[PDB]
Image (cartoon, rainbow, N blue to C red):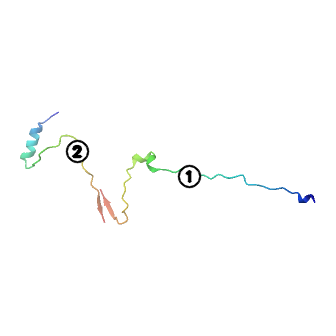
Amino acid sequence: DNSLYSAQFDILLGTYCNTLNFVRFLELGLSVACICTKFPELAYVRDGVI
Amino acid sequence: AAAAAATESDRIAGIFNIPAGIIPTGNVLSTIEVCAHR
């Protein structure tokens, strides 16, 4: 039977993924406008004054 | 320059109970105060 001779098929062509363009804070314009100061311990702070 | 005499200024500082050896004549940078209440 010519039905023994079949070749219809489909294949995947490949896909690309999107990478996220990271933002590093100090390299934006607002960096110099803001003085970012380390102090992890703040949960136990009630009220600070300057 | 000098304006009022630096030696005279330092003498006036000394005589009025301040024992300031050197009166600053220039730029002075002090430390801001951060006060925390816990």
Residue A14 rendering spot, x and y as whole percentages: 69, 52
Residue B27, horizontal then vertical, whole percent: 23, 42
Chain bearing mark 2: B
Residue type, mark 2 in image: Val
Q: Which quarter of the figure has residue A47?
A: bottom left
Alpha-carbon span between mark 2 and mark 1? 48 Å
The secondary element bearing badge 1 is classed as: loop
Circle 1 residue: A20
Q: Describe residue B15's horizontal placement relative to residue A25 as left or right.
A: left
Residue A9's spot in the image, x, y percent? Answer: 80, 56
Residue sitting at x 75%, y 54%: A11
User: Seen in the image, is A17 located left or right of residue A7?
Assistant: left
Q: Residue at x 11, y 46 (%)?
A: B21
Q: Chain of mark 1?
A: A
Judge by depth and name the residue closer to the eye, A49 or B18: B18
Q: Residue furthest top?
A: B1
Q: Which mark is residue B28?
A: 2
